[PDB]
Amino acid sequence: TGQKATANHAAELLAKQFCTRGSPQETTVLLVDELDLLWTHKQDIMYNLFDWPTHKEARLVVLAIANTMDLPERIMMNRVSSRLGLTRMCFQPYTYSQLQQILRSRLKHLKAFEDDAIQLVARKVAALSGDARRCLD
Amino acid sequence: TSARTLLAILRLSTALARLRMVDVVEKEDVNEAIRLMEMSKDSLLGDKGQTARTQRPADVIFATVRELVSGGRSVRFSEAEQRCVSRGFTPAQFQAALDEYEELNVWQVNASRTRITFV
Image (tube, rainbow over all chains, first blue to last red; front, top):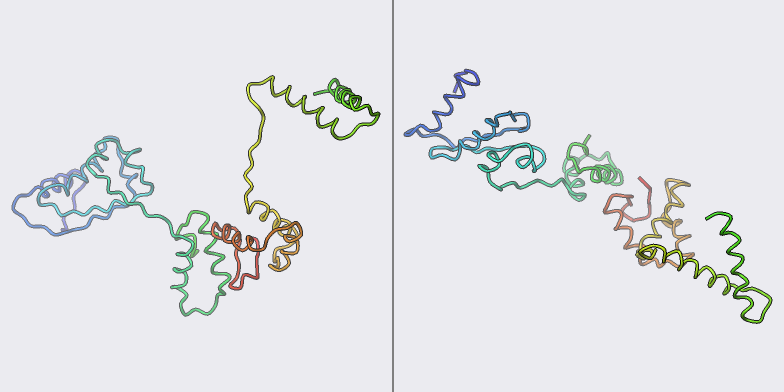
């Protein structure tokens, strides 16, 4: 909407709005990044966020973006990992044959680099950690 | 092991040379003399000292390339084979050994596989 309050005046209106009986909503999407910064001592930030789309008239699609996969079983405790699910599909880094193809798409009509230098740069980054940002730099 | 065991080795050299009615010593009297010493020192413990080594068909191939990396960088592919065929290495196994390390990002070749340079 457009109303701005605070962490308590607003946090109380969002709790009573998701449980409103007799009001249609839309299939929204929630995209959050870096979950370790939202961790508090009472664990009342990640636990209540996952219980919102588990209601009747709730169309929230949470896209929890983080780093490693063992976070729910390390930093977060039992209540956060319970009401979540085991639907954690990790993404593996690019292979050696994939780094030479992504760089080829960017240089489709750029006649300025030999074929012996393209595979050499994509070889050192593939052995370090396979980061997609450490190859084009 | 000090100077006390140094004179004990030369003492066992005459224990076997006098059994063949000869006045000279051969290599048999030396290997059999140290055989009883290695068996006695292993009996003082609770196990036997052995070794473990797997004959990899590509372990000595990488060591031969090391002789050209310390001398230069642009090593010719045809020049590196002047030392591999000296001992008796088959060239058929060398073609299958390059992909074992190039896949794991060690070196790199060209399209004709005629240029090799250590990265």
